[PDB]
Each structure stands twice: as structure tokens, then as C-alpha cells.
Length: 320
Length: 320
Ligand SMILES: N[C@H](CCC[C@H](N)C(=O)O)C(=O)O
Ligand SMILES: N[C@H](CCC[C@H](N)C(=O)O)C(=O)O
Picture: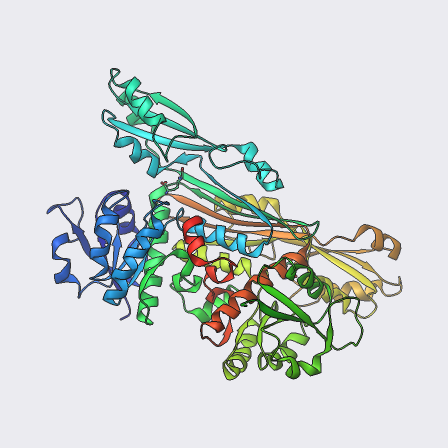
């Protein structure tokens, strides 16, 4: 049948969310997990990542769930040569480059590669584009949280001396309300979000770790940053959740008439929504290839019906 | 240059909104208005609709701004044979049929036809699809207003004896809040919207007109309907606006974790946002055809980047 044979590459939080979610897909079959490790805390079969070539015939889509600001750039293209790949690559400054290289790779193999999926990048990206396209004269703002930013949390974890750490992005409600009225055109994303950190570290390292957090380009400089050092027991019991979300707000004027477009996401578990998007886009990638296409593609180049497990005609008869 | 020669067919509220808005498009040129009437309250050149064939060489896209529940079904296909057409056909039960016929017509002429655009159908349709696709187990509700429904207002105007009339769709805020919590799964759209009518008519016709409103299939039966008869002076001074909007709310569970997706529109002028969408989709239709495609297409089959006046690479470098 047209049941999409799928495999996951890597096995952290995201890989784990994708695994449990692939089960609720009516047209997908998890064939296994490709890992560097021989044993893994799962019932799902595991193969050495180095034996992908041997499985390149039993797997339709390769969900790249390993990487962050490292393993995806270096490793992602190698996988494009064996199957259709879907990644959630979120380094915004590098997305254009990452897509150029993935493209050469995918087109060269005759398979499709969907890059930088998720909710941001991903769902928020699509929303920014549609609203800005439809409203000729517009103002647009993207707000995150309140909630745990995965990108900022692991940036904190890479700082020598940091044992455990979490980062909460907190948006200004005033800014939020002003953006809805079209009164936030003089404000940028750095002025409308406070970044709150909770870090476990030896007291001897506090001064150094704090300066390192505050002067970290891209992630923290330019932002109002709060740094909280707590003992490990407090970290462990009070910071267990992973909620997140945000708003993409666009306003536009059509001649003395204001229009407000707002997309909102309230997620109880951050990696679970990222995996859900990554999955629907893997269904699209196969459809795109199965219908003859190749190379890299951003979420901006996929027609919405390609993500739906449903027949196009049912969608037009029920959803339009 | 690649400045899209465009023309408008018809000239009511929508045609009028499209005209003023085409001016703020950086890549479009209004060539004229095709009308049944010789004279029109505009500076824009007007041609007899019957002379479209003579202009089929000077016009790239034909914005169909005439029709509603009549002129579009009968007339829309004739125009597909002369240029790319964009319509805002909103008869939900007939959209699938309307697209089948438009398709034969467009494919037969080698040009593209974008059907049923606007905000609903249109923007709300896209949102229903994405959220339902990404969230495997989901609940979805569409709320309208508060505001003036154009479809229901002109349905009222067709009732013999009705001189003037307006209809306001009012959604239940309780339902709204319950949908955000995932507690509205037992409710339908008929139970969550009250339909409020303001009608001018001779007092002799009130009883008959009211029964006709209440028993009108599709538009009013099944809904809680309020009918208000007012004098014309009151109608004229107090019911001049055309605001509208709504929410598409989807919830989903990923294993004990809830996710809420909400798309909201607050429009100060209803036809102005419909025209803004219709316009961006006319830019896409040309791109689709200019890149070799033909037949009818719903908003579900257009990749988002096709609506943006901007270069794809700028979008990926700035918006992803
Ligand atoms: N930059 C955003 C987060 C985006 C979402 C996802 N990419 C993540 O890292 O959680 C924030 O500051 O909270
Ligand atoms: N059925 C919706 C309206 C959709 C929007 C647009 N199609 C219009 O007629 O205004 C309502 O009841 O208010």
C-alpha cells in the first residue's frame, strides 16, 4: 500500500515525540531508528546510522531528529542521498545556506528535502508570509512565549560550568496589545521580550557564567536578561515542563480601514508540536516526490493540501 | 515589464475595493473595468463586457467581481476562455461543482483560474486545513463576527417586500472560550452563532417577511434568529458600517498534552479584506500560469510564496 515507510534519525526529545506520534498517523509505518548507539530505551528497532545505505530501500522518509546548531548542517546532506528528509533546522541566519546545500544533494539523488520545519521556523513562517502578502501596507510582529525556548536552553547548556539550565522567553503584554492596535511600529523583537534564565552551577562560576550568558551574541545581547542561579534540587522539581507558544500579529490599512490578522499557538509541550508539523511535512515531501519533484523546499513552497492525510476532494467539499 | 495587466469585471462594493487597492500593488496595472453599463462612476476606462475577446490580448488577469449566488456560476467560465480569472465564489455547497466546470474551461484555454478566494472562503479555509493536518486528533470550530455578513445581507435583500436589510452574525463568547479549552466538541456552528437582522419594510409585510427570513434554508433555519424592523431613516444613519471577522480554533492532544491553534481576523471593512486576498491570489495565478499550469485551483493548492510580490529568496532570508 501507499503506507509511507518512515524512519527517525537520532533519539532525543524530538525524536522521542516523533516516534509516539507516528503511531497516530493512518498512513505511516515506523520502520526503525538510526542511531550511533547500539542499545536504546525503546522497543523500536535500532540500526547503526552508518548502515543507512543498506536500508535506503526499505525507508521512504527520513525524519532528521538530530542536530540543533551542529549535527544537521554537517550530517543532513548525507541523508538526502538515501531518502526524502525532513528537518526542523532552526538557525535562522543559516537557513538560506542550509537549503542551498540540501538542494544540490536532494536534486542530485532525485528525492525531496523539506528544511526548517516546526512552528518557528515552520508554522509562524507561513503566517508571516500570507499576512504580509495579503496586506499591502502592513506592520508585523512575532511574539514568543511565555514558555521554554529550546534553542536558548541548549545554548545555555553549552557554557562551561553550567550543569543544568532553562530559558523562558517572556513577551510584553503591552507590546502585544499595541501591536493589535497598530501602535508598535517603532518596536523590535529585542525590546518586546525579556529572557529569563534558571541555571545550576557552582557558586565559584556564577560571575563568569553570567557574563557569558549576557554577552552571548544572537541569543542574548540586546535583550533584557534576568539570570537566576538555583540549587539542583529546586531545578529538578520546579522546572520540569516544556510549554511554549506565541503570536504573529499583522495590521494593515486599506484606506482609512484597519485589518488585524493574528495567529496564536498555545502549546503544552513544545517538542510535541514541532514533531506534529515535521510529520505532516514528511507526508507532503513524499507526495511531492511521488508526483515527481526534487531538491530542498522550505515550508513556503508546499501547498497546504499536501500535508493533509485526506483526499483533496474531501478537503474542498468540507473545508473550503 | 512583468507588470501584470489586470482588469475588473463588474463594479459593486467588491469591484470598487479591488480598484482602489490595485493602486497600492507594486507590480500591477489596472487596464480597465468590463461592465454591462456604458457609463460608470469612475475615472477608470470601461469596456462592454461583450468586448472581452477584443481585449483578451491586453489583459493578464480578470478579477471577477460580479456574481454572488448568480452571475459567477453562469458567467465565470466564459471568462476563463479569455484570461486568468480570480473569483471569491462563496456558495460553500457549490464550490466543488463550480471548480469542476471552471477547470475544464481553464485547462481548455491554457490559463489558470483561482476559485473561491477571500477570507471565508479563502484565508479561513487554508487555516482549517493546516491545523487539522498538523494535529492528528483535533477538534475544530469556525466562528464569525461580530459583524455584517455580506452573504446573509443580500439573501435578505432578495425577499420581496424587503426595501433595505442588514444581517449581523454574533458568535457566543462562551463557545469561543470553551473551544479554546477543548470543551466545545458537542456544539455545531448553528448553536454557536445568533443571526441578527435589521429590515426596512412596510408594516403590512412584516408577518410574511419574518416567516420568509426564519424558514430560509441554508441561511437561517437551525439558527437562533432575531428580526428587527426599523424605519428607513434609522436604517440609513445607524447601519452604515461593514466590519466583520472571526476565529478558526483547533485543539489537539499529543498524549496528555494539549495544543491550541487560533487564527483571528478583525476587519474594519469586510469587502476590503476580501479584495486584498483576491488580489494576492491573482498574482499567484499568473505566476502559476507563467510557469506553465492550467485549470481551476482552490486556495488549498497554491504555495504561499506565490502570493508575495517579493522574490522567494528574500522571503527565505527574512521570514522563515
Ligand atoms: N526563539 C523563540 C523560540 C522558537 C521556538 C523553537 N525554535 C524553540 O527553540 O523553542 C523563543 O525565543 O522562545
Ligand atoms: N457566513 C459568515 C460570513 C463569511 C464571510 C463573507 N463570505 C461574507 O459573506 O461576509 C457569516 O455568517 O457571517
